[PDB]
Image (cartoon, rainbow, N blue to C red; front, side, top):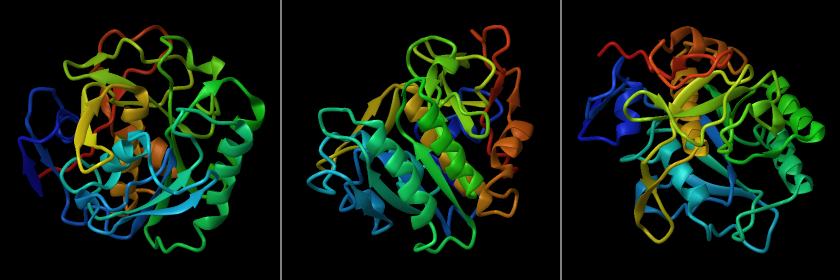
Length: 279
């Protein structure tokens, strides 16, 4: 595969450099892994999702996505035009309101609806969860994240958008998961992006074009945009044999673009999510 004049995010993860405008990948393309987008929900009726998106769970009045973010990121996972893994199912938990917010009661319950619900679904390839969310540090929410990973669900968390050591932010801080940071298109860790010991890989977080509520397709920045790429790739890869739910992060890191970002602090890993598709 070889989708051209692609978003900058997708093209980048297929490329050892920035400055390429075409996305390259395997014909597998996510067919048979599943991904759990944990955020404001999936507008599954989007023409981009071709039936692959759905609302498995919602802790609020409706499954309905009325922010866009849950849809946006969902696209970056498994949209056909904007997404990393273009043949994967997309299982929406709606843990967050349209105010743009929620509780750890819900958040955690979302982590843990999935730890089970994965069962109910079919992913002979493996499952990926996207923590499209983060707050201050809290030791429940981190436990949850672990539990979820512990339970064979490849977890991807945004490092955060506070321009701080992630360690003061959860679920990002949890050792077991893959904590993701953002890069701007010129191989620069993005301004908002958090950092430090904990972070695993980097992704495209910046200017990221993807799906949106009401048929549209817009472009927002954030380290929560970074992650569905990584979950996307995780799911793209776990589908390929190349790794297991546990081994994703440790693979993605072993396979990344080494010393291929700048504006990287001390400690903080210098690696960038690479898909490794020698086309």
